[PDB]
Length: 167
Length: 167
Image (cartoon, rainbow over all chains, first blue to last red; front, side):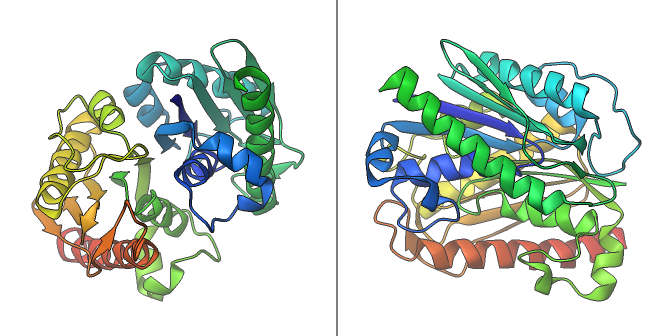
């Protein structure tokens, strides 16, 4: 099968969980509306190996054997980066997942202050994009909007990528 | 702070994600009704290191450096066990995660055919219990109700344990 793993922060493991529910044939799930019935047949050929929510630097570093840059802001509950570092970390997490679990497609996401970053790494190519929503992990400004936008954009891009590269 | 990590299957990382939203002070979240006002103050002292959804045997094994038993049933999208092995696996995952990440409190959950299993392992004690809902991961029979009860029972027990042991 086509195997997928994700290491997600702002999107709370929902990109991986959605991929899993779609693949397994769930008839109701939060982001099902993004999939056509044809997309859902293609998704039966995908298996999720793991979908991790990894807010801790020490968590990410220990589970994936990578090393992350120092946070840009002090924040007790999650590593907190500005945009430049979120883009760097999404790539480092996707790459580390791909090495640790040997999957076809790895997905990293992270967002501190700004639009956040999602990296989708396949066997062929690496895709890196921001969300549409500026938010702030610490003040909570726009954080739910950013989360929902990031999940939707992550899944839309994942489906485009899967179809382009694998179907 | 009190650190927590989770390795969840049937509960979809929602035990750990709920713990994180309560601890970070989210104003509204799906299972907030489980927390009293005093509970939410206590929760500010908790940090989530990772909450992982790990439906594959290979995923759990590689991320925690453990070995799990062979599945009882053939099923493509997730490891599939009888209740006796679910009870073994929830323990093996909670113990492996606590050694991998050195957290105060580790939680594992798994459910195939039957009521499933949740393990809460603290610095002091190991708790292990089934959910209250018989379901079947392969047919989807009652899986939604088992998931909800598993998250509710997991959180309700986690709070009782956190207060008894840490407060």
